[PDB]
Length: 229
Length: 230
Length: 17
Image (cartoon, rainbow over all chains, first blue to last red; front, side):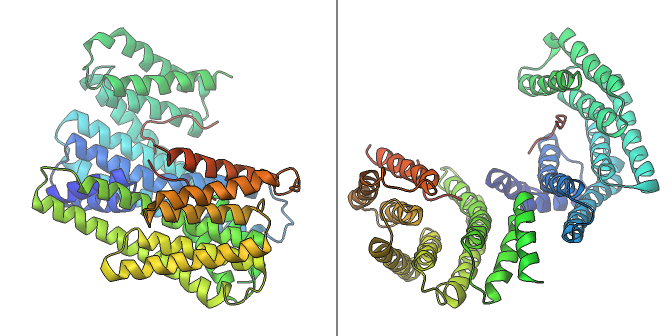
């Protein structure tokens, strides 16, 4: 029964207890049945908030480290802490990715959820790439790229440019081009393409999904303005 | 780990918004038996206030959801069990804090600043317990909160000027205790109002070091007064 | 600054941090 688990997941969401939420959705996912759209959103929100605190913490600690004098006696404590945080982040991303490869992607039945999960794969492989080094960094960046590319093609073939999932995939994939590959022009072109194509057919968009698509598009042109500086 | 490095990691954890680690550090420092500076005490307060706060807010959300109508006895059972789990966590946190206070901090403080700070803290966490308590446990928790608060209040009034930030914050939290725990809005209003009036009375003589804090606290007193006058 | 990405993260006033 996923019903009680979903109930608890929503309670946790409103209570901002995202560990509990991620537990609930992990259990549901492991029951083996395909996830509905609300349930996919619950999974994504849960693990997004779990990993988020560690991404931000890691950013802070790393910033402090790289602005600390190398001869400082207090450097190794900073290092050790950053490495602990990084370890937790790796643990979480690995959990998500195992959930995707073992359950969700293997059993996804419609293009919407397949694109959703592939996008997620790219997102969390990207979260790993942000903190990886050496060959590990090469291969993790590669996996992220591949997930994003597959999801991108499928979205182009099976969805409208106004679909919130397609738009979000374009947003995050552009950010992958900017922060990871370091090609700001291509990231700008992804964002602008998605935005223009969305406005073109904004009239074929669902009233209920309107708020979501609008939100994403605003993030897209926000990114565009930023990067163009 | 040495006290110095424990502090270093408490501050680093605070920068990282990782308050469980911060609270663990400061708990270690406190258990080492060493008296804490003002800075270190504030690290303790920030850490544990952040740890407990999430539980308090979650408990509020879940409780509110529990009062929703037309809900299945089954779903209601699930909601209540979750609220009970959060309750358990909260009680554990407040318990740890109070064990630190009674066992180390309050015990080894003759200094009025520290004595008032720790007694106030005790009143705070016993209040956090009182807002989720049942039956006789409830009356005991309330009496303990009120007692600690009262002792802090007396010590402050005998040892600290009205403009001092701990005296003011103490007045603030003690009056919120009167309003929310004892449901005596009149005495809460007079408590906060007396604090504020006594502060403004001696504001021109306040030093420019504690001005920044006591002004903010005073503004909180007035906020609560205005809110409590509907 | 950090680029934006899709999935993102009355009472009485007591003494604060």
